[PDB]
Image (cartoon, rainbow, N blue to C red; front, side):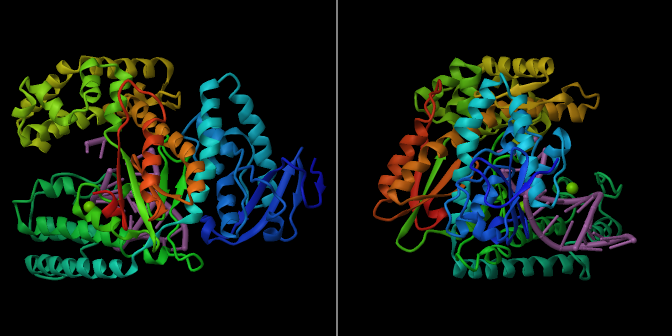
Length: 540
DNA sequence: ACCACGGCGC
DNA sequence: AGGCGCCGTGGT
Ligand SMILES: [Mg+2]
Ligand SMILES: [Mg+2]
């Protein structure tokens, strides 16, 4: 019943804190408190009081550690019931949600957050009793990873502001050309960013066929699915798509980046979240690195903005084909495993297995087919979309999917076994036992059920790839710290480091070894490494 | 400002 | 290929 004692707290208290805004690097610490045995201790001066703690334990511990690091304090994050909640069920992604689900309330008062953290931790710890695989993940991956991520977020990355000015101008110049042409074809200016105004132009004024409908507003859609089907019905459609692409790039990944350069540090502090996704993959925000375009040369132009400090270099490491390697491991398909053991081009081999021709006879269009099939099958691409993407009949798409499963029958078996297990147990799991609940496999609606089926056989693969990277980051960090090198960015299956140019080569060698050897699979883990003054130069 | 929403990236 | 972070719009 509310025992309130003075600051400082006994060792092993849980902390609660309130920030002026959600982003710790940019926030003022408004209040700080700790709780132990349900006894709450409120700090009189929060920043001063941070020096009394030896670690941050509690909800959003990593975020307090980032802010402490900004302030020159080494306050590592430790136990956090968010990590436990996320292990129990990855739909647990926010403190508000976790309190709602398991008891208590996420409020705006630091003492209450401290008390909540303590009770939630005990509760969730009990709920994990006997779950040895999740507990292994907590101890070997999640808790130690949180300290790595704190350092990554607090360190940040240098941007090339002169380059971004030049890129901005170039893109602005092309947007203006496209804009003028859309208006010339429409016969009058209008707001190209307004889908409502664009709907009226395309379908009422120009009279084009309206295929699809919006999802909730019930109007004629102007989505790329519609426009693609009309790219010939009128030249304005192609210009709209080009304009949309550039404006999305500019407004998302050019215009906002310089404003994200911190006044104190001179660096951009991408935020990393380890309890955000269905699969266990790390997420980033401000900016979201995952959605920098990867197909287009546009994406490359953004990566070029990320540069090393003067006298340093960036080292970029990528797990080549890790999703397919994991699929090979999980399915045990001996044909797929052989491709990788033999160190062969996986798409050329797939093509040559698929088509029963020698690898020398595989032409680029065949390799493109194999590549699309490889990932189509992984991601649950339909025959209809496959037929669009390769520009072949629908029946030929169907045949090509069946040819793949004939060649890789244990991949077919594994997908069906995985769906059966998910339907039986209500969840699927990764190699390490990270678990995702999949209730909608029972869904009545075809669309919703099929989405659940894709999640069911994607999560084991994606989440194994995720935890391999996360384990590798945990293993690598202490070794980099000792070389005076640092971890900066993680996205997809890639890790970006920064090191003094004198030690960049040795750092690369060390990181490649650690990542390739993180865990033994039925196939080799292969890491592509590059070194450069900017991220584009390092990963090309 | 707040919100839901279309649209789009992965 | 395939839940959500992101942008700008239009409503209040
Ligand atoms: Mg685009
Ligand atoms: Mg929405």
